[PDB]
Amino acid sequence: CVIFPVEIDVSQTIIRDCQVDKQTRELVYINKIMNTQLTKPVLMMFNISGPIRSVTRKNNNLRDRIKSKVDEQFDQLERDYSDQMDIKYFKDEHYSVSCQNGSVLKSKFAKILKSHDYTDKKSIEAYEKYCLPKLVDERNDYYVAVCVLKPGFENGSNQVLSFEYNPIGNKVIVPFAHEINDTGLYEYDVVAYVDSVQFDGEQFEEFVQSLILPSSFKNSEKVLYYNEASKNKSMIYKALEFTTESSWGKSEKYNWKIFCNGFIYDKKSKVLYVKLHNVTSALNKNVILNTIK
Amino acid sequence: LDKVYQMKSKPRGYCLIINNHNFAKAREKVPKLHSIRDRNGTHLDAGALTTTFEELHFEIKPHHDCTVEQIYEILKIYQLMDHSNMDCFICCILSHGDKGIIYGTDGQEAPIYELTSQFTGLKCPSLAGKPKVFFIQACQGDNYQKGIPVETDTRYIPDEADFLLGMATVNNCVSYRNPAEGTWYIQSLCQSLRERCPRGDDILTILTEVNYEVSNKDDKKNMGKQMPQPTFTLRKKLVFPSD
Image 1 (cartoon, one colour):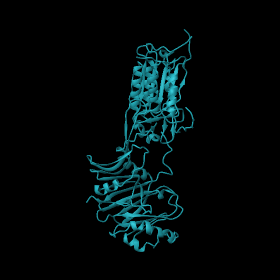
Image 2 (cartoon, chains in turn purple, orange):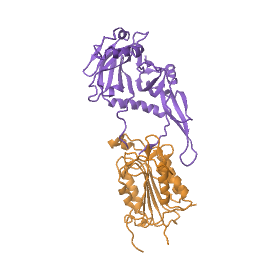
Image 3 (cartoon, one colour):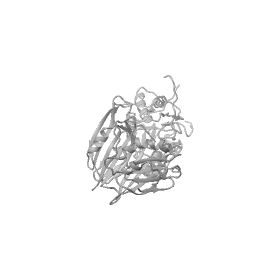
Image 4 (tube, chains in turn yellow, purple):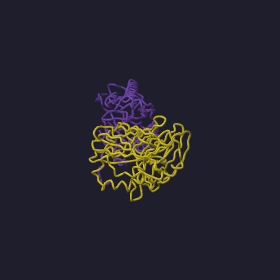
């Protein structure tokens, strides 16, 4: 009943991280930049628990399959009453990934055999001040994935990237970190699907709580914070709520609950659903977890 | 001097209310219709029309989630029936649709012509000369209707006569259904009916108001507009009094 949706506008960020075997996990990453016709070599980077043993290109169908399993989980919380109808390279032609030991990246950074050269200092210089500092820390481990999507990446499908890596220390670092900006505030637009990890309401209350939800343009709107722990669930999230009135007959009210963003955990399944859709927070950090030990 | 459709019959007439909610069978089979949701809220209108045409002395005859084939049968039934003691026959279809068609639980279309022509004077001699009303709450295209700024406010009779056809929306455009309250057309059709019927106004008058309301209802989101559009081949004022 409609076919003019999602196009050159649907591009938040979709990340899935699941455990493939004993000491191996696969990371699927889909961001805005990966879905656009790049004309120049683009660089992006993040943190991974361990080192990358292989990199591959998955099919875009994967983007919608991940955003569904998640968007649905947070959808059973909402009450939207809107009107409906009836030293370790991984080269390739298009990209080039490099996975070095966090600290090592700082010391050698300049070295761009990943061919992000012609961007010269006037371009790399930037990343050392606004991103790099937010990728390396007192825990010199934390491997840094260095990716360099080179033009041509657009041709064909399979824009999604996948990283087969070996977790060091039972740690999992779902990459939410951004590029330190002058302003001080960060906007989040991401959905995540990580599994085989143990809950942790200490760092989730912290995050969710520092979330500033979008406005529904209603004076009556109140943003509540939640912390439920149902049967096989435990959700930490914030919703924007406001009551509405009938449009015809009786005086029946309609309590809305929308813009739900937070973390939902499946106590049984041991899976973690993340949803930070267009929410702002002064907190620009990564979510670290522990693999079911 | 004058003329008005006879409405005396205590049991005015039947009211086949085909309420379609689950389009699962369709999301599977018909490929194009896999990204199709269910019509949530339809129930509010189903209970809305039932309440309305109740005080209006109509013997409502509700029908679950019907598939095209069932619908046709349901209609082929109330066609061989006698309606002599009945002075009016109403049919309401609620479900998804497209260009002059009404999807069923299954997922295959069903041209309106093939539904409404099932009750001509020939096919049903019993309803000949008696008003046959049809209200079709469904989509009729993928296009959204734009909204322009008004800045104001003994013998033989034809075979297809006495027909009233209420279209939730003009053609090529979309109908709007709200999960919490119900659907615009159907809700206005009632709020406007259930109120104007006491003061004795024909349906043709009442539908003009309905066009007024739904024309004001705006799809806050995608700047949408819905514009109902009836069609009739009636011969006298259609009006039903109550108590």
